[PDB]
Structure formats: structure tokens, C-alpha cells
Length: 201
Ligand SMILES: [Mn+3]
Ligand SMILES: [Mn+3]
Image 1 (spheres, rainbow, N blue to C red):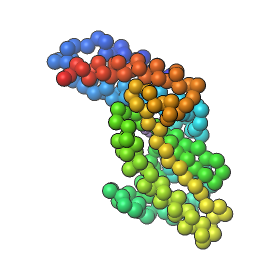
Image 2 (tube, rainbow, N blue to C red; image 1 turned 45 degrees about the vertical axis):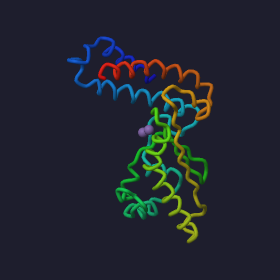
Image 3 (cartoon, rainbow, N blue to C red; image 1 turned 90 degrees about the vertical axis):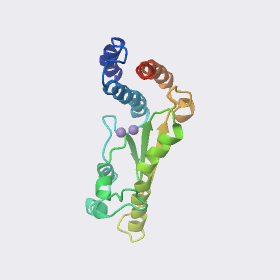
């Protein structure tokens, strides 16, 4: 899988200069590993759960797909998210791309996979990004519900699935028979990651 991507990588590392001349960007390498590091855990979700088995899909299209009339959806396209640091316009916030989602009837759920060493931060980092404007939309539905322009009010759900770089909590974050597959695939890349990190400091 995304291991085939890690494949094409671990090449470029184990042959390396000391970090003095080195690879000026171990970063491009580094970043690459992270993407892969994220994708392993994403993949697992994309099997056991998600509606998008393909790719992460924009929030606009999620909405239509949950059967919310475009004319209503373009309704909120010009508004602005409450308590936003950036003052985000829902227009933009519909181009946003969370990793995984699932519709069931009048309910919509997102799941964001992240992985760092700092759990709450990643959780914090992402909540800050989505949960603000997701409640919004949900609310701007009931608001549109109590006027009866929809049959049913929609419930919406954003959870972050975030896993220690080691994997220890994947027990608690995402129990799956794919688990033990994932933890081990992580360990491998991690060693690469750390290595590139220990070649600087
Ligand atoms: Mn993503
Ligand atoms: Mn993510």
C-alpha cells in the first residue's frame, strides 16, 4: 500500500551523508515519511468504516451527498464562522478536506486522522480547524429546520482519531483486526524518522 510509497523512500535515506553536507532537505524526505505515517492509519480507517474508500472528499460535496439542497447550501456559502480566528467564510470551509466521512441517513460524521507525539495538541490543532464550523452548519440546519425547509434536522459529528507515534493507544482509539498490522508498519517508518532527526542535533 502506502508502504509502496515508503518503499521508494527508505532507499533515499539509508544512503546518506553525515548531516553536514547530507540532504539539505531531509525535510522533503521527512515530510514524505509523515504523509506515509499518516496514510497508514488513514487507510485502516478507510477500510473498516469510511464512505470514501478513495480519497478525502470536500465538505460541500459531503453535504449535497447527504441530501441538503444546493440552493440552501449556497445559502450559507457567503456567511462567516462564529469565533473564527480567521473569520472563515463557509464558502471556503466547504472546500476543506477532512480525511474520512460517513453518511447514515440524516446523520453525517467525519473523522480526522492525525498522528504526532503530542496527542492533545493534534486533537486541539484539528478541532480548532473543523469543529468550529461543523457545529455551525449543523446549527444552521436546525435553524433551517425550525422553519421547516428540510424534512429532518441533521446531526453532524467530527471526531479526531489520533494515535501515539508508538501506537500504544490504538487499542483505545481504533480497535480493529487491522490494528496489529498497523502498529508494526508504523514502528518501521518511525525508526527512519527518528534516524533522520538524530542526524541533525
Ligand atoms: Mn487530510
Ligand atoms: Mn489529517
